[PDB]
Image 1: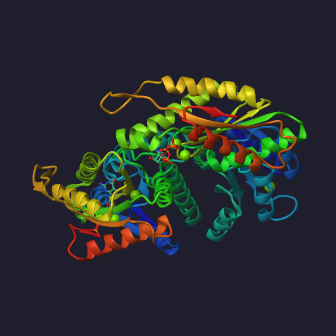
Image 2: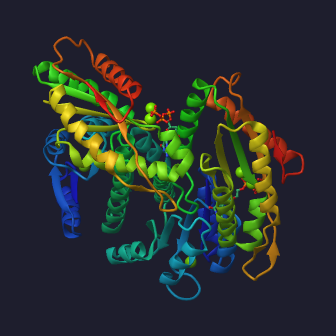
Image 3: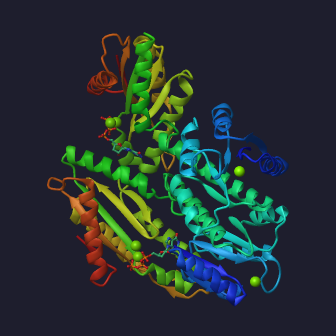
Length: 293
Length: 293
Ligand SMILES: Nc1nc2c(ncn2[C@@H]2O[C@H](COP(=O)(O)OP(=O)(O)OP(=O)(O)O)C[C@H]2O)c(=O)[nH]1
Ligand SMILES: Nc1nc2c(ncn2[C@@H]2O[C@H](COP(=O)(O)OP(=O)(O)OP(=O)(O)O)C[C@H]2O)c(=O)[nH]1
Ligand SMILES: [Mg+2]
Ligand SMILES: [Mg+2]
Ligand SMILES: [Mg+2]
Ligand SMILES: [Mg+2]
Ligand SMILES: [Mg+2]
Ligand SMILES: [Mg+2]
C-alpha cells in the first residue's frame, strides 16, 4: 500500500507521486538518498521507486544502500532510468533490484511494476509462513501453531485435561525500533524468545505468532498456575538491562492475556484465542507490563 | 527456459523470437491460438507472450483459454498489446495474466517481464508443492492423501489389483514431548518419516495423516507382505538410539494396523481406513510396538 519515490527532479517526483497516489496507493517522497534513508527506517514501505541517476555516483552505491537500511532485511526496488540497453537490466538484478522502468515512465508501466513487486512480496510471504519454525527466534510460526492449537484443544477436551493459552505482545515495540534501530529491535525479540524458551516446562508449546506477538500453550496447566509462571517471566523481562547501539541501558516489558484451564464450557479453539486476545487488550488498556486472566 | 510466442504478424513474431532466442532462452512460435494449444499440451512451457489483438474473439476469451489448456493448470502469461490505458492492465490481471508489455515491445522490457514471470512461476510452483506436502516431513499431507487414497482405490478396483493400507501412530508420543520438549518430538516425527521414505518400494504412497499418525498405501501388495515390510520398519524404529537435548538416549516405537489387499468386498476407500484404524486400536490395546492385520 505504501510506495517510496526517490527522484531529485521535483516535477518528475511529484508526477510519479500523483500517479501512485491516484491509483489507490500512498505516495512517500525523497529528493536525495539522505531523506530516503530517514523514510525507510521511519515508515514500513511496501515498494521503492529509485532514480538510477542521482547526485553523486551510479546506483551500485544506491541499490545496495537501500537494501541493508531495510528493517525487515529485503524490499522490492523498481529501477527508474534512461538506460535502454539490455545489459543495464542484468546489472540492476545482480545489484539486487526487483524490477526496471525505462524513463520517461508511463502511468501503465509504473502500475504494472508495483503490482508485480507486491505480488512477489505476497508469494514470498505465503511461502516463508509455510515454514515450521521462525528463522530469527527458532519458535513455531503462526500456521503450524494454529494446527497445534486445534490438535491440543481437541485432545485436552476429549481427555478432560487442563489447557491454558497465553497471548503476549511487546509493549510499544515500535518506539524501540524508532529510538534504537531495527537491529536492537531484533535483539529485544530474540531476548524475549530466549526467556520464553528457558522458563516454561518442556510440555509448553511456544510460537512467534506475529512480529512481536507470542502464543504459548500450557497442556495440563490451569489458568492460575499458567498466569503465575507467565507473570514471573513478565517480571524477569522488565528487569533486563538491554544495551542500545551506543551502550545506553533501556528496559522493555510485555502485556499478556491467559485463557482456558478447564475447557468444559469452551466449544472451540477459536473461542480460546478470542478470550486470550480480549484479556491481552484489557492488559494493554490498564497500564501494560501486566497479565490478565 | 522455454517461452511461447503467440502473434499473427510474422515479422513481429520473428523479432520477439530473435530477442528471446538471443538472450539465452528457447523461442517457441504460434501464429494462431490453434497452433498455440498444440504447443502447451506438447512441450513444457515456462512463460507465454500473448498478442491481445488476435484473429477471433477478444482476450478475456484468450487468457482464460491458454490457462486451462495447461496440463499443470496455470502458466505465467505476459500480455503484448497497444492498449496503453491504465484500466486495461487491471482487466488482464483479473483475467489471470502475470504481466504486461505495451507494444512496440523494447528488448529490455521483454527480458524484465520474462525474468518477473519466471520468479512468479518459481514461487507459484514451490507453493503448489507445500500445499500437497507436510512441510515438517516432506511426505503427503492429509488433504492430498485423502484424494490419492480415493484415486488408488478406484484404480485398483478397475484393474482388480491388490492395494494394502497401513495406519501407524507413535507409541506414547505425548510423554516424549513432555519429557524431552517439542523440538525433540519434531526430530522423532522426522526420523520416522526418514525410515518410512527409505524402507518401502518406490510405488508406496506415504502420508503424514495427523500430528503423529501416518498412512502408507502399498499398490499391488497383499496384507501379509505389507505386514512383513511394515514389521521390519517397526523393528528398525524400536532400535534407533534417539538423543535428547542433553544427549540422554531414549527409544520410541509405533503401532500399526494393516487393511485391504483384495478390494473385491470393500465398496469404498473409507471402509479401508476404518479397518486399518480398528487394527491400529487392537495394536495399541495389546501392548503397542506391534502391527495387527
Ligand atoms: N526489529 C523488528 N521489528 C519488527 C519485526 N516484526 C515486526 N516489527 C515491528 O514491530 C512493530 C509492531 O508493534 P505494534 O503491533 O505496532 O504495537 P507496539 O508498537 O508494540 O504497541 P503496543 O504497546 O500496543 O503493543 C512495528 C513492526 O514493524 C521484526 O522482525 N523486527
Ligand atoms: N513435537 C510434536 N509432537 C506432536 C505433534 N503433533 C502431535 N504431537 C504430540 O502428539 C501427542 C499425541 O498424544 P496422544 O493422542 O495421547 O497419543 P500418544 O501420546 O502418542 O499415545 P498413544 O501411544 O496411544 O498414541 C500430543 C502431542 O504431545 C507435532 O507436530 N510435533
Ligand atoms: Mg533525476
Ligand atoms: Mg502487536
Ligand atoms: Mg506491541
Ligand atoms: Mg498481431
Ligand atoms: Mg494418535
Ligand atoms: Mg501415539
